[PDB]
Image (cartoon, rainbow, N blue to C red; front, side):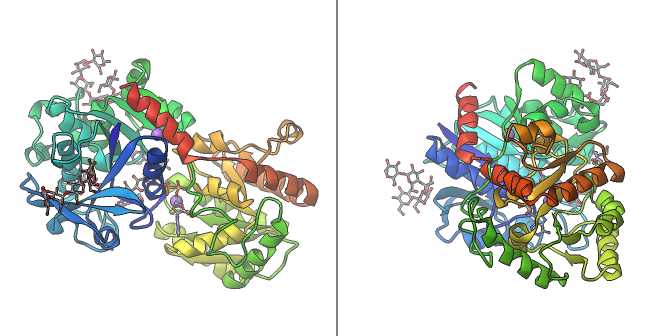
Length: 476
Ligand SMILES: OC[C@H]1O[C@H](O[C@H]2[C@H](O)[C@@H](O)[C@@H](O[C@H]3[C@H](O)[C@@H](O)[C@@H](O[C@H]4[C@H](O)[C@@H](O)[C@@H](O[C@H]5[C@H](O)[C@@H](O)[C@@H](O[C@H]6[C@H](O)[C@@H](O)[C@H](O)O[C@@H]6CO)O[C@@H]5CO)O[C@@H]4CO)O[C@@H]3CO)O[C@@H]2CO)[C@H](O)[C@@H](O)[C@@H]1O
Ligand SMILES: OC[C@H]1O[C@H](O[C@H]2[C@H](O)[C@@H](O)[C@@H](O[C@H]3[C@H](O)[C@@H](O)[C@@H](O[C@H]4[C@H](O)[C@@H](O)[C@@H](O[C@H]5[C@H](O)[C@@H](O)[C@@H](O)O[C@@H]5CO)O[C@@H]4CO)O[C@@H]3CO)O[C@@H]2CO)[C@H](O)[C@@H](O)[C@@H]1O
Ligand SMILES: OC[C@H]1O[C@H](O[C@H]2[C@H](O)[C@@H](O)[C@@H](O[C@H]3[C@H](O)[C@@H](O)[C@@H](O)O[C@@H]3CO)O[C@@H]2CO)[C@H](O)[C@@H](O)[C@@H]1O
Ligand SMILES: Nc1ncnc2c1ncn2[C@@H]1O[C@H](COP(=O)(O)OP(=O)(O)O)[C@@H](O)[C@H]1O
Ligand SMILES: OC[C@H]1O[C@H](O[C@H]2[C@H](O)[C@@H](O)[C@@H](O)O[C@@H]2CO)[C@H](O)[C@@H](O)[C@@H]1O
Ligand SMILES: O=S(=O)(O)C[C@H](O)CN1CCN(CCO)CC1
Ligand code: NA
Ligand code: NA
């Protein structure tokens, strides 16, 4: 069984969020579990730099101009690179410029990614053809469309990591992407008068998955589907929609072996976590104090994440005696909001605006609680990281957060299953109740420790996930 993942990022070469973590860890797991998995990526500069054994497979002309298909290895896994400097040789985000504007040629940049994915099924590499093309998010949404247009020389799976990003482009681009004009149709890739790459992925794939079981249910509802729910409801009925929960990469996210930490520690040596907390406090300029709970954020600042609620709840949290340590980049409204708060409450609020890979580890390793108040959550990895690190996640009960965290309710404590704090509604009052719950647990240190150990017993294995994907692949 040969599978090609078609996507636009991969840890550690290029990462803007959780997607890259998946692509960086799933293929290796699949290989261990008996699937021959390779990855197709655009040759963004950081990716091209990391693959040092890249060889030429092929040159082709294309609706988007010429490509050199390269192939090499990263961390044991076979990586194809689409080298097209005129599209991909630019620094920064794969999706937008410095000023945060989407590239105006995105339709071509990402249509090409989908086209090469499909072309791979027809022998673009003379030495290896995938049986299944596995496309990820809107970026790769056209891959199943190109496959359909060519009589499905391979089966296709489309997985949604996020339904809010739709890959909308004006209809006139049907002229630019070499698909049948008849594909522009509610029964096809049209979506409210435009082209949608997400719609294309959802419509044309043999099978759709979402990155958690409850998000797979949620996206059949108007609240989480943003107009797409009818397709998803229909695909559910056809048995063509399912959820497979993400794992965590243990090579990189384990306090037991984490080389980025001041101090490594284990589920049975949580005393060794304290030095991380002290150095985190020092690093952020917080009062060095171990009697006080340190709450943390490591998050893209976008609407999805509910961080406005954190801002509203901040006074309440501070009033109860908590500290906050925040790392994130996105909306300036949010950015300015938090910078202001750190100015207003020095020694209590530490903030760092920007993307810092190593610093997120030091936060995860030193904080007591990780705040994930998301409005929606296809899966969420940072809460999984909190669990592994004994950093209790405080989450909204939605999507993968609902699949993965157990509230410290009386039943859950009594059954030995409690692992964090859960609130229901997207408002600060709801958030604040969960925060109070945390303060109550914090005043019973042995109960806190009992919940940490249970959080750290939770297992999120990629090889276990690989097994589900494999069953899926064989049943197509
Ligand atoms: O894609 C298959 C899927 O479609 C619906 O689910 C969602 C859809 O995928 C999504 O794109 C969006 O649809 C909006 C669309 O983008 C807009 O263009 C507009 O749709 C209008 C159409 O453009 C227009 O052609 C016409 O549609 C008629 C169809 O052409 C016709 O074939 C017929 O199809 C119906 C089938 O008979 C029925 O079995 C099927 O389940 O539902 C179809 C009806 O939608 O009838 C159509 C209606 O006359 O008018 C359209 C309505 O103005 O607006 C669209 C809705 O906002 O959102 C969709 C819902 O989330 C279907 O719900 C889903 O069943 C199907 O699998
Ligand atoms: O210069 C001499 C050489 O030149 C040309 O080969 C080049 C190819 O034309 C070009 O495509 C590229 O080859 C890539 C290949 O496309 C890519 O798929 C990958 O090949 C993998 C196989 O996919 C994989 O199956 C495995 O092959 C095994 C094979 O299973 C086994 O039966 C036995 O043959 O051992 C093989 C090698 O272990 O591994 C290979 C290698 O990873 O990578 C290829 C190499 O980069 O680049 C080629 C060399 O530059 C000519 O076409 C060729 O005939 C000439 O001999
Ligand atoms: O790995 C994290 C995240 O990456 C992917 O999301 C990207 C979107 O697909 C992409 O459109 C882009 O969205 C941003 C716009 O470019 C920007 O103009 C502004 O609108 O903010 C948008 C939202 O952030 O950037 C993100 C990169 O994070 C992927 O699809 C997600 O599943 C994934 O979780
Ligand atoms: N500002 C940041 N600095 C460093 N890492 C970040 C930052 N923001 C997010 N991350 C990382 O990105 C990933 C986010 O994954 P996830 O929680 O699934 O959410 P999403 O995919 O929606 O971004 C995590 O590895 C997280 O640590
Ligand atoms: O996401 C912003 C914007 O994207 C699309 O507009 C494209 C357009 O399709 C291209 O032809 C060109 O003008 O560049 C734009 C950005 O990539 C959507 O069509 C539009 O609705 C959306 O707001
Ligand atoms: O992120 S939020 O949940 O707070 C807001 C919604 O996700 C806004 N969406 C839904 C789909 N979009 C198109 C507008 O319907 C843009 C992202
Ligand atoms: Na999935
Ligand atoms: Na994030």
